[PDB]
Amino acid sequence: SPRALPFGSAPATLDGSLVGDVGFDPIGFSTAPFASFNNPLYKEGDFMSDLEWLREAELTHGRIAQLAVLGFIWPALFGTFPGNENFGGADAFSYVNPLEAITHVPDLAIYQIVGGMAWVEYQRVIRIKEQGKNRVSGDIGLGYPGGWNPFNLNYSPEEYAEKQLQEIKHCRLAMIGAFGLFFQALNSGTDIVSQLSPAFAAPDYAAKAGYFLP
Amino acid sequence: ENEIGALAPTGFFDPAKLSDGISQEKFDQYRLAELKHGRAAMLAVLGYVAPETYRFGYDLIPGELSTRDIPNGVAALNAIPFGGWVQMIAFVGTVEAYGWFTSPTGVLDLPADILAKRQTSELQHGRLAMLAFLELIRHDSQNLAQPGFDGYDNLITGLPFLY
Ligand SMILES: CC(=O)O[C@H]1CC(C)(C)C(=C=C/C(C)=C/C=C/C(C)=C/C=C/C=C(C)/C=C/C=C(\C)C(=O)C[C@@]23O[C@]2(C)C[C@@H](O)CC3(C)C)[C@](C)(O)C1
Ligand SMILES: CC(=O)O[C@H]1CC(C)(C)C(=C=C/C(C)=C/C=C/C(C)=C/C=C/C=C(C)/C=C/C=C(\C)C(=O)C[C@@]23O[C@]2(C)C[C@@H](O)CC3(C)C)[C@](C)(O)C1
Ligand SMILES: CC1=C(C#C/C(C)=C/C=C/C(C)=C/C=C/C=C(C)/C=C/C=C(C)/C=C/[C@@]23O[C@]2(C)C[C@@H](O)CC3(C)C)C(C)(C)C[C@H](O)C1
Ligand SMILES: CC1=C(C#C/C(C)=C/C=C/C(C)=C/C=C/C=C(C)/C=C/C=C(C)/C=C/[C@@]23O[C@]2(C)C[C@@H](O)CC3(C)C)C(C)(C)C[C@H](O)C1
Image (tube, rainbow over all chains, first blue to last red; front, side, top):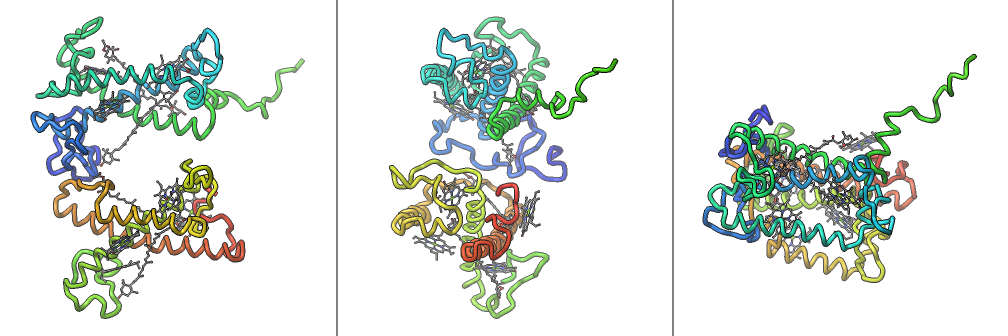
């Protein structure tokens, strides 16, 4: 196991089951049944692989957390909260602190995005419940080679391999980063712009005034 | 009785008759016991530290008696109503006799080598947590007496950043 270099992995952890198969699985819960834990829509049929189900789990989490990162920076930096609400500055642009932004925004848009991801997972289950064989992260049509939407994916199988690698890695690293940003802002009551910009500056306490010299 | 439960500190620590005799007749029972004790005391230590920075906002007696106000440490025991802790324990005892959640099933495979090593490490950690719970309770009560009889006032003497 090169990730955990001086250690052994599961008696049956695979190297080709998922792209991210460097062997990192210290407790390696992959070994455990990883089945329809508490009846997780049990199928007993193809049922993918229990490892592959944990893989779909990591994929969903990392994808959501990746989007979450940009939703922690762009509200501040990129677009500077283009809330541009017809009225009601609160629950809009004004709350640039992401935690406070959630604190304000009415349950209208909350239920909007809730039903959005609800239809998302409804279609995901609709695929995967039938999409046996290779569940392949419940891919279905979503930007697949058939490209169920615009610019239907036009790449090569080697490019597809590299792209799977890109996605998986970025999702894992973003799963770290979202934790980062969240604990940051909560334990500072600010937004990332605040601490990072006074950091890249010179404190007002010491500035050597200005070059008022003759 | 020289089974798992021994390491470099002592090959069989039992400076009394305690070990010898009841050969596999009390040794397994004592393993059950020490296991349960060490696990619970580990949970205790995690208990003490976690109320110091975080606090779940639930109102134990609805309307009032909100977690955010009850003292941490031993003082909660005096606070927590007798019957309230009785109901809490009754849930715990049902859990012990029903396996309700708390990983009701699922322990992976863990081949016998790694499994034995994990079990030994478990025993050692829980044993240590027993002593950790001891020191904590000691300090707490002693301070409760003369406010800073021990000296260092803040409850968790180490981990100074918390307090
Ligand atoms: C037709 C269709 O729809 O199909 C779709 C398929 C699909 C795949 C959706 C498509 C695509 C590609 C997509 C969406 C790719 C998205 C990738 C995304 C969004 C990847 C974010 C990563 C963020 C990470 C890793 C973390 C970074 C940041 C980290 C780790 C930090 O260090 C943050 C740090 O902040 C702290 C923690 C503290 C600060 O003190 C210091 C700094 C600032 C340094 C298409 C093309 O749209 C088509
Ligand atoms: C299948 C399923 O669903 O899940 C799985 C999940 C998983 C993980 C696999 C499972 C497991 C195993 C688990 C959960 C193991 C958990 C182990 C755990 C939680 C172990 C804590 C040890 C803490 C110690 C030793 C603390 C010592 C602390 C000590 C010695 C101190 O110094 C205390 C000190 O206090 C003083 C005295 C003074 C203070 O001034 C300073 C401090 C505070 C520092 C299960 C059960 O199989 C179920
Ligand atoms: C969109 C948005 C919001 C949001 C949001 C949300 C919901 C963000 C959520 C982010 C989320 C959901 C982040 C999850 C991280 C999970 C991690 C990091 C797991 C790591 C687990 C690790 C590192 C463990 C690795 C292991 O090796 C270990 C240690 C033992 C091994 O045996 C087994 C394995 C291999 C497992 C607000 C706040 C609502 C409004 C705001 O305005 C913007
Ligand atoms: C967490 C929390 C609370 C709590 C709690 C709870 C439930 C805490 C539980 C604590 C618990 C369960 C603590 C066990 C200790 C067992 C010990 C110390 C055993 C030692 C035994 C020793 C040292 C024996 C050593 C021997 O060598 C001898 C001497 C002779 C040899 O022949 C045999 C051996 C080698 C064995 C409060 C207080 C209710 C409220 C608060 O707010 C929050």
